[PDB]
Image (tube, rainbow over all chains, first blue to last red):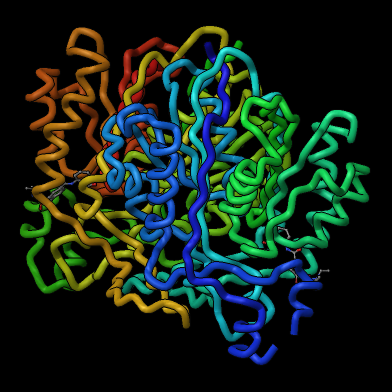
Length: 319
Length: 320
Ligand SMILES: CCN(CC)S(=O)(=O)c1cc(C(=O)Nc2ccccc2C(=O)O)ccc1Br
Ligand SMILES: CCN(CC)S(=O)(=O)c1cc(C(=O)Nc2ccccc2C(=O)O)ccc1Br
């Protein structure tokens, strides 16, 4: 019994809802934002940090699935906006829910973090040493954004979602391709921390607040992510695709390039905008609560993420 | 042929070298004060390199020493809690600088247990049959995260990195592992907080990024929980050497006594490097291979055990 499947899904975002309207009044930018990106509103934290969000997801997953915290063999969080560098968010969550038996760590892979982490989760299970784990992508990008730069401030939201993953009799994780190219890392940065020790003599002026090269990542998505997807499926072999919800125009393009039915690409960024590592799991959980996807349906679903790094990767799983 | 094994090791620390003598003039205290407390004589401190650079060198050296081509690498894991950016990972930055164009890459956050956590992870990856060659580097630039006025913590840490090449093998090398965590104590050991000053945030948080360390809580923690962790894998009979996080030799002394394992088997490293966090074990590992103390493909029973922020701890039992 070596195979793994997703056994439960859960999401949690902050109740504070911020509209393009609100952001524009505040910024001076009207809903060219929506036609530009497919975004209408995101959720923004007013009191929560990232562990607060991931906690909720962890708590909900235990509730809905009816497992004890002590069943969890491990907890991976894919974030790039953790409360601290140390402790990891996962350790904070692991404490908060009393999963005494779990080891936990965070995975740093930007918008690919949830796919990378679900992939690593699958390996931890295939080994036979671990049966049950929680994988959660969570992010509070609002504390990284320079809110007076309308270029990006409008793009990102805060949120969190994840899944419970347990061992199974039959395979579900069918294939995967994980890729990266740090020869283009310049294109999407955040969270630089400046060394001001008495011994440091560099005066590097990297930003602490997020910064992206808009044209580069966009171009990178269409060409590279499209090839990565086609590396796993054609239209005949996939039923749905949950892509990192970073821009609806990317979704459109990737669909035409890949010749995969546009209908099959679920969308979400209208309500949540770009929540990075959280984006796929949020979408996933909505689609399940919508009734679009059903655990055990055997629907053929590919999850594909892409973002800073640069990183990208796809999973083909039968649900 | 799906068993990970360590096929090569290497390490890199900045050139700038800060002796107790120096800190003691700096911090206005004595040579002996520093030494008595830490058990350390000198340690390396960056002056122009970030974690990504220290890891770069490591990867670079593992490539040259193993005579492997970067294009052969399938994955790069970096254990670090002091990255250049949160995004991109140090792992990716390294992956760019060495043209490992075929490898995917990410960071693992698990503080002073990172290397062990990460090594464990590479085993699963290789074990799956999807990947055969990977770099697993622990590197840390913790000097940027200390209040250098405080002789209490700042005299403890040094910078640097070091890691291993892992390759697929016919015969299993990784025998047993136990990874543990206790987030109910995460307050004990913290760094790198980052305050939300968004226009929407109405919370009220102070936030030195500078480390906060509850000394005796984590000292007693290490002596108790680590010991029990080490014993669930081996006893004195079934181990040749143990590579532990180099936090403070007195922890290594007390743990030896609890486990009832020969003290000479616990390799020790800290005089000249100080506490290098995720770096500590893989640097100890490369020195020991220099000495010839450890010999690759000898079948020496070895256990690498880490413990640190989280709280995290964990041990790998592998055959060298
Ligand atoms: C030609 C596209 N341009 C406007 C429609 S844009 O470059 O300004 C732009 C371009 C992107 C983009 O390509 N984003 C990403 C691409 C890959 C991975 C992650 C992202 C992300 O936004 O997180 C998002 C928003 C805008 Br506005
Ligand atoms: C009672 C112990 N005291 C002096 C012997 S101490 O708190 O100053 C101290 C206490 C520790 C310690 O307990 N460190 C750790 C414990 C668990 C995990 C990691 C570490 C680490 O320092 O990396 C290390 C050095 C000193 Br000096």
